[PDB]
Image: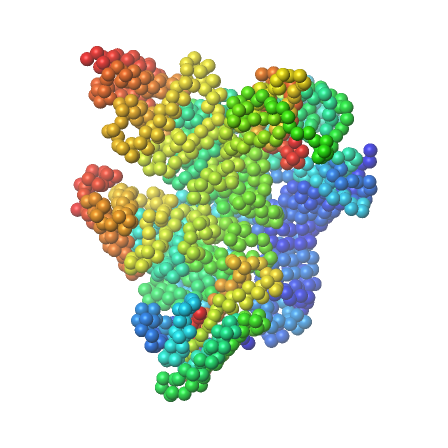
């Protein structure tokens, strides 16, 4: 490789390099300044002998006359290896922790390749997250894209950490792993993850990509593609059940508009780029099972809904690429419910694939619909009680009201460090159904009531 | 052979010089990889290409080759029972040649099998003057469908040499002496997806399509060549209705197009569609089905050109004289890809963040379907029936692509999630759904079975509409405080809902209801209402009717399971109803 | 007469012809493609020896080098004649009813001319439409601009056909004619009017301009 | 440099609660040494009196008050009523432990933007020495309006309500520089920068 000392223009984070040949699109560069500082970069546009590059660390303090540009000849790559489990990396894959650097088995582009539609396999087996609101009512399935919608200041970092600790497959012949990708989060959240993952030993089953909020916007955009590249490697080449957790996905969209505003591009809805639906789909569709392969990729993207609005572009477009959502409400968090999961607006489109005998007990779908319908009338009677006092509530309306109270404090509120097995979750659901009289339980078949109902 | 040189690569835009021979909208192979690209703008020898795949690793100085043709589709033996993407790349053969479960870029493969030996049986006679569309032979491509070889457009001359033998789609099968000179023909022809196949004459569809689904074929029928819009809400069983139409409709071929979809939803189609069984032959349904599968991660151009590739294939079999049914899922995700392509072209934003020509592109799609007089001296007829699915975020039907679709199509099967929760399948709202073919189909129905079928459907719908108005009053005063005429109307409507509208697609007999079986089934229900109402005006209480009519009502309820060769058991109900009712008033 | 083989640029639906002379604004052109396909277009901007034109049928598959542009010299016109009564035309005015084309008395710009405010006359006599609401609660007058606001799925198709048949003046001292203009409608909707006008005989006193939805947007504007 | 943070050995989790003296804060809504806190401070709410209580009875060693584009009449109040605050222990003027920065609204725009970066850089210098510093930003909203002015002067793409699209990144760069860290040296001394903004 030869150095190029021809820098014609320096306009913001962009930089013009001239008299070059053999330069490709999106390849990495290194900039050597008068001081000797090294700064990574990426080619955004190249025509004839000219070349336009964008520097990650910034453009401050660069003299065009006494600087040079090195073209590495490769795009953004990740050195994949089986030794990445138990290690913390930065946004682009450098050893963030003070550990021995890994020997890469190979290098892969972060963009990856599209999965052949005939080669993708359907989701079948059920993933036990240990959380009653996500194992019973909104089941998670191998290869499903089930996100979590949260608000600013809500305990979604404890929820994402809890699932990474408790997620498991009920089969012996399998290797389970978690790819935790922090995206533009603060140091205090980053310190919470890294400390908790080592406190509970979950780091021995995880590959963490920590990207801070003061990190450059390019690394924030590359962080999901980096983690998803390591996820597809462990699942499709090493045959492992990989669970991907992304936080925060709203920060990812905030980085796209910041980049799109620098590129002078035309904004779409709410100023976000028109290609936000597709750029997000490039990430969320990098999951699922493949025929003949034992490994699989499951994604749980966590995003914070701006202004707690579901019609916002970021939560809306995510619903068009994912198979459901897990809603976190502040009202439940105000009552100490942990995790504050509102089961009424939450949904799993693939929940029917990992339920029933052989994947769960025979009463999974039955108690799911009964608990859901009973919790609906309970909160309907609670809301009706504030309007016209507690006098207008009937006997069953007061029974369902007490059901909704106990359904929140004893069933949903389990604690961020309580790993309920699937049998405990179902047995507990029957204990709460014992509050209601047997006549109210219309959906549950009579044979099931005689077997499980206390 | 002319090769261009890349002079600029900026994201999805690549400009190349030495492109004087190329024309607008031509496909290209960009760079050493040869990634697929399309010429959007061209000034002098410098063309501006919109690259469809990733341009990473492509720079100036790399060669660019123009295919000399727009986005086309290979049409010949080997196209049936194959799963393609939007640009019609064979996913089956692509996976074998690549030897990987993923889609590499630059891998260019022909759509059809150019090496397979097909037996071409010639039906034409030498010396015959042939024009476009004239059939010169056929190939037994599948056990269900006979692929007919026809003279391509632009060819007009006298057949000089025709022979029957096993050839590939590349071997010349026929020699024709045109006015310019001798020209050879093969079993495969190419056609641009953005240009409609020429027809002799277009005819309005006045013949109803027999889907065997009672709620559809009776109240909201579609005609061979019409278009129906189905909205897909989660849990409504759109897949079941789509499957029942794909296998029970009296169409020769079925074209399924997936514009964009979740990888798990598209996988559901790839697995469940080949398992559908053609009722008549007993073979797999793929023997008469061409499938197109795309996902969100796939290139946007493949997602945008998905419906144009599938409707060109349907037009190809339409010209042979077949009845084709094309289903798109989802047109909304197709419109999203259309808006993303519009953003890459820096076009002006139209209403609600959609290109201003959104209604035009939708109109250009549905105006290619319909009953036509195909080319050729035979003057044979063919049809294309469009069954498009609309998926609106939030479920709102006022979204632009639905209103523009509903402005063109005449049928709408409003799926309802609230009906699916009540175990009402097919979950089709009978108040919100409509069909503008109901009047013409009713005239066709009265003629074919020599009965007043049109007057029965209107009454059955009038009873259902009266039930809705009574339910509002019921919610306010109660069910007991109603006249016996109102009480009878609710039970008549309950019979229409449970005994006619609701049918299980998995039941061996109830999955398909013939036209004559639909008639007798609706007649015995309306006959019960007429004889009960007439006796109600003779001093008979509503409770008294239901008391002595338990045995007959149950026989009416289970009439949906009566076999087709036992319709006499459904015709004798009317005589039993009449004798039972007059026996009650006699007591 | 002149055929121009000098096409410089083809950018989207617009072409750029250079080394031209005598081209006027909104002048109708005719593009001869390299495959014999003929596409007509209009001039949007002309400067010096250059000319910017917009092709009606589109720009797909046009090679700049092997294509020619023919400047006709006249704007969009219409061949007017009394023989148009009982004939069906498209958006551009070309025959559509499989009938012999008729020779016109003269050609007129479709843009029309503004009526002199003093030469214009006030509407004075009412029109019998046959509809109770149009003839009583409301009333139609000779020379009035009375539109019908409708919606998707509403039977505004049958109403417009009903008025065209039942429109007459009492007593019929002078002749009455109906000019029906279909603007970007579907085929089944267009075939409805053609069959209804010929069945009832209303075609004998009417002229029909039918423009489909799949027709170019330029034809939809000129209809 | 004012737009570049000072190097540290490592940043630590802020866990030591700062004794503010105010019962409502220290009991229900506390802030640790190196933590951040936001204040609306509407009209008549008395945020002027509250800021002084946090500036006097806080166990921090240094106070850095920064005014980023504040009203002049309001600014001249802070100028007057700050050398009057007595220290709880020593009894001297509070300016013996305070570095003040004042910008009027009609002042140059870039000065109002660089104000928030000047105080946080000065606070980092006192933090490297091992002291616990507290920087008060009032009012950070006027600083956001300074960016909205400079973005228009550079013809940048508008974001939400006209504010630039990198408004969140600039705010993130500010609060991420503050906190309990380990300063550079061969003794590993500890400092902290608690951020209070209005």
Residue C80 found in image quarter: top right
- Between C189 and C71, the one nearer to me in the picture: C189
- Between A213 and C168, the one nearer to me in the picture: C168
Tell me the residue at 67%/51% (across/down): B15
Give residue A356's position: percent from left, percent from top. 29, 43
- Between B49 and A261, the one nearer to me in the picture: A261
Tell me the residue at 39%/80% (across/down): D56
Tell me the residue at 65%/63% (across/down): A16
Give residue C34's position: percent from left, percent from top. 73, 36
Q: Left or right of C187: which side holds A448?
A: left
Residue D37 found in image quarter: bottom left
Residue A397 found in image quarter: top left
- The vertical placement of B69 against B11, above or below, is above
- Between A140 and B481, the one nearer to me in the picture: B481
Q: Left or right of A407: which side holds D188?
A: right
- The vertical placement of D75 against B253, above or below, is below
């Amino acid at each position: 490789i030869k150095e190029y000392r021809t820098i014609k223009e320096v306009v913001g984070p962009l930089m013009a390099v001239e008299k070059v040949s053999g330069v490709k699109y999106e390849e990495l560069i290194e900039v050597r300044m008068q001081n000797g500082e090294i700064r990574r970069g990426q080619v955004l546009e190249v025509q004839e002998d000219k070349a336009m590059v964008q520097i990650f660390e910034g453009t401050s303090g660069i003299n065009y006359k006494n600087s040079s540009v090195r073209f590495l000849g490769h795009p953004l790559q990740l050195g994949v290896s089986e030794d990445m489990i138990g290690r913390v990396f930065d946004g682009l894959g450098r050893p963030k922790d003070n550990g021995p650097e890994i020997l890469p088995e190979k290098y892969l582009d972060i963009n990856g390749e599209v999965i052949n539609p005939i080669a993708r396999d359907y989701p079948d087996e059920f993933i036990q997250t240990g959380i009653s609101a996500i194992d019973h009512l909104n089941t998670l399935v191998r290869g499903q894209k089930l996100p979590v919608f949260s608000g600013s200041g809500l305990p979604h970092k404890e929820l994402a950490a809890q699932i990474a600790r408790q997620a498991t497959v009920l089969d012996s012949s399998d290797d389970f792993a978690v790819v935790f990708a922090a995206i533009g989060i603060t140091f205090e959240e980053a310190e919470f993850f890294m400390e908790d993952f080592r406190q509970t030993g979950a780091i021995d089953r995880s590959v963490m990509f920590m990207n801070l909020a003061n990190d450059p916007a390019i690394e924030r955009i590359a962080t999901p593609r980096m983690a998803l590249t390591a996820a597809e490697y462990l699942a499709y080449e090493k045959g492992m059940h990989v669970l991907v957790i992304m936080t925060d996905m709203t920060n990812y969209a905030e980085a796209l508009r910041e980049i799109s505003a620098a590129r002078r591009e035309v904004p779409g809805r709410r100023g976000y780029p028109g290609y936000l639906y597709t750029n997000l789909a490039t990430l969320f569709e990098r999951a699922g099972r493949i025929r003949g392969l034992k490994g699989s990729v499951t994604q749980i993207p966590i995003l914070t809904m701006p202004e707690d609005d579901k019609t916002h572009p970021i939560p809306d477009l995510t619903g068009y690429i994912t198979e459901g959502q897990i809603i976190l409400t502040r009202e439940l968090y105000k009552s100490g419910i942990q995790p504050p999961i509102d089961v009424l607006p939450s949904l799993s489109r693939l929940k029917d694939k990992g339920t029933g005998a052989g994947k769960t007990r025979e009463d999974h779908a039955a108690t799911m619909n009964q608990l859901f319908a009973a919790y609906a009338q309970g909160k309907q009677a609670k809301e009706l009680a504030v309007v016209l006092g507690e006098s207008a509530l009937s006997d069953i309306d007061k029974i369902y009201a007490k059901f909704a109270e106990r359904f929140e404090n004893e069933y949903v509120n389990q604690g961020f460090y309580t790993n309920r097995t699937i049998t405990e979750t179902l047995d507990l659901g029957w204990e709460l159904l014992a509050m209601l009289p047997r006549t109210e339980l219309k959906r549950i078949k009579d044979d099931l009531l005689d077997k499980y109902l206390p | 052979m002319q090769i261009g040189k890349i002079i600029k690569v900026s994201g999805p835009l690549v400009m190349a010089e030495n492109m004087s021979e190329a024309s607008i909208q031509d496909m290209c192979l960009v760079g050493d990889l040869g990634v697929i690209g399309e010429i959007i703008e061209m000034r002098q020898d410098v063309a501006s290409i919109q690259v469809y795949e990733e341009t990473s690793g492509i720079g100036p100085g790399e060669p660019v080759r123009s295919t000399g043709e727009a986005l086309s589709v290979e049409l010949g033996p080997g196209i049936i029972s194959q799963m393609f993407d939007g640009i019609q790349r064979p996913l089956d053969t692509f996976m074998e040649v690549t030897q990987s479960n993923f889609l590499g870029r630059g891998v260019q493969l022909p759509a059809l099998d150019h090496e397979k030996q097909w037996w071409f049986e010639a039906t034409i006679e030498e010396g015959t003057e042939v024009s476009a569309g004239d059939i010169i032979g056929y190939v037994d491509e599948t056990k269900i469908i006979q692929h007919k070889i026809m003279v391509p457009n632009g060819i007009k001359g006298t057949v000089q040499k025709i022979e029957s033998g096993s050839f590939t789609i590349d071997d010349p099968i026929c020699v024709i002496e045109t006015e310019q000179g001798l020209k050879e023909l093969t079993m495969m022809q190419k056609w641009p997806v953005r240009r409609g196949r020429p027809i002799k004459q277009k005819l309005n569809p006045d013949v109803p399509m027999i889907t065997g689904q009672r709620v559809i074929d009776t109240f909201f029928p579609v005609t061979k060549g019409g278009a129906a819009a189905v909205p897909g809400p989660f849990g409504a069983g759109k897949t079941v209705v789509q499957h029942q139409i794909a296998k029970w409709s009296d169409v020769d071929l079925v074209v399924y197009v997936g514009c964009g979809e979740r990888g798990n939803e598209m996988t559901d189609v790839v697995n469940e569609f080949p398992e559908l069984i053609d009722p008549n032959t007993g073979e797999s349904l793929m023997e008469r089905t061409v499938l197109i599968a795309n996902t969100s991660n796939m290139p946007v151009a493949a997602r945008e050109a998905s419906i144009y590739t599938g409707i060109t294939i349907a037009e190809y079999f339409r010209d042979m004289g077949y009845d084709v049914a094309i289903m798109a899922d989802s047109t909304s995700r197709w419109a999203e890809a259309l808006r993303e392509m519009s953003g890459r072209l820096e076009e002006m934003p139209g209403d609600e963040g959609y290109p201003a020509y959104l209604g035009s592109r939708l109109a250009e799609y549905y105006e290619r379907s319909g009953r036509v007089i195909a080319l050729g001296s035979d003057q044979r007829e063919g049809s294309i029936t469009a069954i498009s699915a609309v998926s609106p975020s939030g479920g709102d039907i006022s979204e632009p692509v639905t209103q523009n679709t509903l402005r063109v199509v005449k049928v709408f099967w409003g799926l309802d999630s609230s009906l699916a929760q009540k175990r009402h399948f097919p979950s089709i709202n009978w108040i919100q759904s409509y069909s503008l073919y109901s009047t013409e189909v009713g005239r066709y129905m009265d003629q074919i079975l020599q009965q007043d079928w049109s007057d029965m459907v209107t009454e059955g719908m009038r009873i259902l509409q009266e039930e809705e108005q009574l339910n509002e009053i019921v919610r306010l005063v109660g069910i007991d405080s109603l006249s016996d005429n109102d009480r009878l109307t609710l039970e008549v409507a309950k019979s229409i809902r449970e005994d006619y509208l609701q049918q299980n697609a998995f039941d061996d007999v109830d999955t398909f209801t013939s036209r004559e079986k639909q008639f007798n089934m609706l007649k015995v229900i309306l006959t019960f209402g007429k004889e009960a109402r007439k006796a109600l005006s003779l001093g008979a209480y509503f409770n008294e009717i239901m008391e002595g009519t338990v045995a007959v009502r149950e026989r009416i309820s289970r009439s949906k399971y009566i076999p087709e060769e036992e319709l006499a058991k459904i015709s004798s109900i009317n005589e039993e109803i009449k004798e039972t009712i007059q026996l009650i008033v006699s007591e």
